[PDB]
Amino acid sequence: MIREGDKVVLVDPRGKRYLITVSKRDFHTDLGILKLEEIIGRNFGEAIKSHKGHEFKILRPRIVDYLDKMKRGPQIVHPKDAALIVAYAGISPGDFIVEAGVGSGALTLFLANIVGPEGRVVSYEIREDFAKLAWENIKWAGFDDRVTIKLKDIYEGIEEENVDHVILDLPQPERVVEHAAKALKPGGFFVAYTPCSNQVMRLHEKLREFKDYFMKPRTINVLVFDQEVKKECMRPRTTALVHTGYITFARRILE
Amino acid sequence: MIREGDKVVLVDPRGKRYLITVSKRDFHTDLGILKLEEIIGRNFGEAIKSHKGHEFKILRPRIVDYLDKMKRGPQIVHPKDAALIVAYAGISPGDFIVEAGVGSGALTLFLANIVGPEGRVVSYEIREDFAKLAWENIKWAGFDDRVTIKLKDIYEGIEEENVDHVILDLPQPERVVEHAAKALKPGGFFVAYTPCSNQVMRLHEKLREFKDYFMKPRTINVLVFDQEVKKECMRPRTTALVHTGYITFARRILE
Amino acid sequence: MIREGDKVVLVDPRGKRYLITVSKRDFHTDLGILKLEEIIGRNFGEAIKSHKGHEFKILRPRIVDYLDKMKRGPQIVHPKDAALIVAYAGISPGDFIVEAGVGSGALTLFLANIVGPEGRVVSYEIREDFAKLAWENIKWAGFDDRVTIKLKDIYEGIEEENVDHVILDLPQPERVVEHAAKALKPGGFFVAYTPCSNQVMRLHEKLREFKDYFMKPRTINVLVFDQEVKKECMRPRTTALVHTGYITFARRILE
Amino acid sequence: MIREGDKVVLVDPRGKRYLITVSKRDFHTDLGILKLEEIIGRNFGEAIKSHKGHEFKILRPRIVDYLDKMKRGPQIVHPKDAALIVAYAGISPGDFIVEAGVGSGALTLFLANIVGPEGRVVSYEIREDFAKLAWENIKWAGFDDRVTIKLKDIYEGIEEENVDHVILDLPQPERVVEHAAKALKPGGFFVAYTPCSNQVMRLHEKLREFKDYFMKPRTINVLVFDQEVKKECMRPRTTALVHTGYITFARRILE
Ligand SMILES: C[S@@+](CC[C@H](N)C(=O)[O-])C[C@H]1O[C@@H](n2cnc3c(N)ncnc32)[C@H](O)[C@@H]1O
Ligand SMILES: C[S@@+](CC[C@H](N)C(=O)[O-])C[C@H]1O[C@@H](n2cnc3c(N)ncnc32)[C@H](O)[C@@H]1O
Ligand SMILES: C[S@@+](CC[C@H](N)C(=O)[O-])C[C@H]1O[C@@H](n2cnc3c(N)ncnc32)[C@H](O)[C@@H]1O
Ligand SMILES: C[S@@+](CC[C@H](N)C(=O)[O-])C[C@H]1O[C@@H](n2cnc3c(N)ncnc32)[C@H](O)[C@@H]1O
């Protein structure tokens, strides 16, 4: 059963989610006031009603809830891009990742979830304000067990050794190629997300310089179309998010 | 160090990978004969040469190697689609998944890797020939610790209870909606991959019938463009894989 | 030189266009009042200023100006789709086209421009209110020389014979296939625009029935991405119009 | 009726087209020998049979036939891109176009068709071998009435004045911006097709330099998806042509 201090997701009659901590306080919504105390001693799958009689269904928070409801500061990496980073670099339970910059911690949360409680993520960040926001998100999602933030400029070096992956979302990933070459295990991946084609060009210039340290690099971009499926009309949604950034992969190989 | 019986990835001078078991035998390539015995007692990152003097670099097999080099029978789910299944359903270490049909086991391998050694995948399959091929792939990748195959028609029922996700790649996923509703935990996901728009239509008809058992369903399709980045010319690759199948998600919610 | 009663395009300092008729009246803008009389006796390429001193440059109206500035009622066919209709059916100066329904006349204007003053477009329309709006657009663009509107339900028949193309944007183009087969010249095109995949399915069912009257049909959909090209960053625009409708072509062939 | 020396399209039972000149000779196909003399005195829509009894249906050649069946040398501009050039620049019957380089004449044929017999295209070309091939295509399609080829390097200047459009497919369109500014009518379009993002960047650098000569430039790229529509399965075709080149438009405006 659910206890005071536990987190839950409440789903309103419109399907909207609220990720809350269970306490003895009132929670205000546009559908009325909820007495959060009523959740104590209930089980997931049950429901409570607001003072206006609207039902809120109780679910266990999942990674999708934390990602969707986290506090956002610097531009987050979209789940579609995190998905392809994890898929094409083969990111796996138990991996050791160096990430930079932590930003809001959205990519950090996604990677931390995948690596599991015995994996490790060390995220570099130069902006101490952003690092504080990210750390609040990380603690909130319960991933302070496996994530550390370093307030260090990663262009100056990577301290960690025998790293499975170096995953980058910062302006000049070319400034990290040499450090990543040193830090990565044989067969580990360097991955960089970059909004601009200019950045892809600069990164590939640096990867060509370091050609004997990596397998052939690959750059992709991912588009996800939503479909509208009504009884009498299936068609793609009219508008889509067609660009976030390019993703470049290079697998480390010795000599 | 590497021992006889261990698996390794050998990378040839063109960057081509071979996923092999280390034994005392000759391994024939288009670049000459390798004495696999020479790998015994070496460490990852080292290399051996063929009888023609071509170097093969030694790497630890990762999930990407098993997925790329597995034996294929029935049409596999592409990594881009597996990536979005895992991302948008929040598939996580420790999850319990019911999958059908196992097919070649490509999606099974991807999901098994994500759920980790304490997660579980039960994959249903009606074709015993396909089930045998998939099981060989699963044992080969070392995931027989966490995957079971059931030779059962899933349209007749799901035996498992309190399942995190029901993940489908078969012709008529609408025939599984009612069973999945029963099997899924509150907040668990039903996910179905379907090549044809006709199938999406039939599935949504069934999900509308079961509207009080799920949150609003979402159907997507994912396109991944490769970029060609040469010193004097960056452009998308001329041709792309633009369609594999649609992916439909519906999260279980009670009443 | 420009005379009273002529149409001109005025381009403001932000690049915004106004398509106006030259008269002796004041024209109000957010950048001040223009004395349209000042345009009489000027030549294209010259400019006038508003009472606030903002310059408006004078250009000859082109088809792009009429299409961009026309009055819109029923949903117009987007220029990208009209472009592919004209390209893949080979629509040419001098052609005779039957169109339905006229709608706002956007597609009509595009086709009328391509066929030129010796071509002909007969556009069918059942809604007399829409037909009036379209006819105002057609007269405004000066294409009443080559376009006729028929207030007739095209599902009941096409009166015209030896037609180069039958071009459709209405809900049930399958109801026009038999009539188009009769009306079209050998080698002429039947073309239908349809937002929904369901409509494409119904249309292809009818085209299969009429397989001995047409070459193999082809259905496409067209996506146009805008690129943002700043000095330090080139990337696709973040959001795009990814779906308007499918376009189906079938070329008439006898027996 | 058809006369000796006329061109016709013959359509075989598989739907394949042959664009031929009618003479008294044998024409060999994989479906047998045709006696082209049998076409003399027939009308479009009729048919002839090969010596093996396979029927070939007779159609009047249209622009789509000439474009599809022309001789190709240097890489042609794809019809989808020509379509958007014509649509977004508003290319119209009677226009005067300067094009470079002529290449194989594919874009030339498309533009010549649109401008009609009273329009004019002057195409520049430095390779005399390519110019000869293009001119053969142009004469073959009957557009030598309205197209001229100049064996001149367009980077050295445009001789023509009061041009409606300058349309470019060559490596360094930035070298033509100043000449086009001089040659174009007020409101005329400069349009350039460029495969590489690097070229788009260089072109926009030059257009920024010439900002007071043009309206804000726009760069697009066009993707056309084919749909497979079978009775029991509609889906996009698996593979598509996703990249040919970017198209940049800038409309001329004085001062
Ligand atoms: C786009 S944000 C990262 C967003 C993050 N991927 C997420 O999903 O929330 C880029 C981050 O990189 C940080 N950064 C930039 N240069 C850095 C450097 N040299 N070392 C460490 N962090 C850096 C910035 O301060 C910023 O927080
Ligand atoms: C497209 S294959 C699955 C491919 C798989 N996702 C992969 O990545 O390798 C579809 C599989 O579903 C199996 N199948 C079809 N209907 C089924 C049913 N009712 N119960 C169990 N398996 C079924 C087929 O025999 C086949 O192996
Ligand atoms: C989507 S609007 C056409 C928009 C038009 N293509 C444009 O670009 O402005 C569809 C039009 O078809 C007309 N229509 C529907 N059924 C028709 C019929 N059977 N005969 C003639 N017009 C019809 C409708 O009244 C409407 O004006
Ligand atoms: C890609 S091809 C043009 C293909 C053409 N658009 C078609 O559809 O067939 C480029 C052409 O530009 C010509 N060219 C390159 N530089 C030129 C220049 N400065 N002046 C004239 N022609 C030039 C080349 O010789 C070549 O024939």
Image (cartoon, coloured by chain):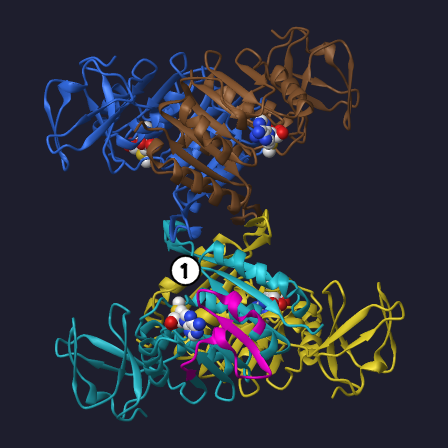
Chain colours: A brown, B blue, C yellow, D cyan
Residue B46 in view here: yes
Residue B242 in view here: no
Q: Badge 1 sits on which subunit?
A: C
Q: Does the numbered disc 1 mark a residue whose Cβ is under 8 Å from ligand 3?
A: no
Percent of width and height locating residue C116: 55, 83
Q: Give the residue type at disc 1.
A: His
Toward the viewer: D34 or D245? D245
- The quadrant of the picture occupied by the N terminus of chain B is top left
Q: Residue shown at 57%/68% (left/top)?
A: D88
Q: Which residue is mark 1?
A: C204
Q: Residues within 10 Å of mark 1 (few under 14, many from 20)?
A: many
Please tell me in which quadrant of the rendered image residue A86 appears.
top left
Percent of width and height locating residue B108: 34, 25
Please tell me in which quadrant of the rendered image residue C136 appears.
bottom right
* Number of on-image labels: 1
Toward the viewer: C205 or D167? D167
Toward the viewer: C83 or C39? C39
Percent of width and height locating residue A180: 44, 27
Is D26 a magenta residue?
no
Residue C166 is left or right of residue A218, and the answer is right
Percent of width and height locating residue D196: 45, 56
Is D161 a magenta residue?
yes
In this rendering, is residue D3 above or below A114? below
Q: Which residues are magenta?
A: D149-178
In this rendering, is residue C215 above or below B70? below
Q: Secondary structure at mark 1?
A: helix
Residue B236 is left or right of residue D57, and the answer is right
Q: Residue shown at 20%/86% (left/top)?
A: D36
Ligand 2 positioned in quadrant: top left
Please tell me in which quadrant of the rendered image residue D182 appears.
bottom right
In this rendering, is residue A251 above or below A200? above
